[PDB]
Amino acid sequence: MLTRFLGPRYRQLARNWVPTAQLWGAVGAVGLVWATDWRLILDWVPYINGK
Amino acid sequence: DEDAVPTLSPCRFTGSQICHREDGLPLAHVAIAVEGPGWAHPDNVALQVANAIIGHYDCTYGGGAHLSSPLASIAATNKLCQSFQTFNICYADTGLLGAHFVCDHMSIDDMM
Amino acid sequence: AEPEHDHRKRMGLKMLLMMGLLLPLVYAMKRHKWSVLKSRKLAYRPPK
Amino acid sequence: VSASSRWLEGIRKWYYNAAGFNKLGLMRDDTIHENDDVKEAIRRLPENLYDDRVFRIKRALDLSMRQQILPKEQWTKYEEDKSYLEPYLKEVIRERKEREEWAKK
Amino acid sequence: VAPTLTARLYSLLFRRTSTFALTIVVGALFFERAFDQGADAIYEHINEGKLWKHIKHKYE
């Protein structure tokens, strides 16, 4: 019954938190990547090619 | 006209606290504010609209729980105060922007 | 008796270099928050 | 009265200065350890003393925090040290002992 | 240039706990590496007791 959250205001609310939720994903991405020294991802980064 | 007519120098806003503790009074008064732009700044209108959204409250207000302002409504429902008011005091180039409130000794935290 | 000998001393170097950066840094963080209590001024104003 | 009293008095004045609470603007009775008898006596103090006592203690805790001390001028001189709490405490003890005597019978 | 440095740093990267975090994580990446270079380079300079031994014994 998630219809309670369906309306104009809720839609404005979602847009307002978008940049924040996006940036929070940027943090989690780099966060995992750096913490596991992601071979796959890190190779693209200049200066972090310690091989 | 002529000599001896000064202009006003801007006033430095500091951002600090002054607590006058007195347990003999039965309700606490608290007034918090940030630095406002001052008279001429067009920004005042928008500031005034946000304030209006928070608004005011007083214990004799009819309609408590159903009030639009979440502050007011939560305030009224949990009896977190006797009154509150937002404000925007304008001076040349500076101002006080905030709210003032009156409440019981055990409600100051929640109200804040 | 201690094959690790050299490795630890490398970490030890890092441990001193790191702590030589973290220590003052945390101090200043703690200094900054206690700021409020270090400079607080009191006044007593009794009636009469 | 003579050299004798002054000597004990000066031995006392010496310890006092050594105890060093006066450096924090405190008074002997401010440092008293709070127990039941003491709590009651603190309770019986009249408004003025109770207020002064709290400010004194606050001044001290505040100093003991930044580990500073008061200017020499403002230390609390022996002599000038008021045993404000004493009479109250004595009466609180004197009351308790009465219940205690009564409890033996 | 100097006040505006700490300022711009606050403006573009510090308010939003988002960017504030985005930067420290990104700042931890570059740092971890640059620290391990200098640190090891330091460990080497005060030594030279192993590694250049390799140039001798093998190379085949």
Image (spheres, coloured by chain):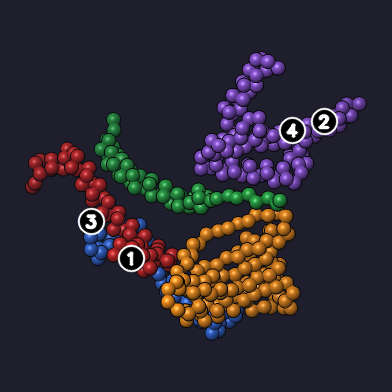
Q: According to the rendering, which colour does chain E have?
A: red
> Disc 4 to disc 3, how far (Cα)?
76 Å
> Disc 4 to disc 2, how far (Cα)?
12 Å
Q: Height in image: B14 above or below D46?
A: below
Q: Nearer the viewer, residue D73 or B54?
A: D73
Q: Is residue E50 left or right of residue A30?
A: left
Which chain is drawn using purple?
D
Q: Nearer the viewer, residue E39 or D12?
A: D12
Name which residue type carries label 2: Arg
Q: Quadrant of residue B88?
A: bottom right
Q: Height in image: E28 above or below D20?
A: below
Does the image show residue C45? Answer: yes
> Disc 1 to disc 2, how far (Cα)?
71 Å
The image quadrant where one finds the C terminus of chain A is bottom left
> Disc 3 to disc 1, how far (Cα)?
35 Å
Mark 2 falls on what kind of element? helix
Q: According to the rendering, which colour does chain C have?
A: green
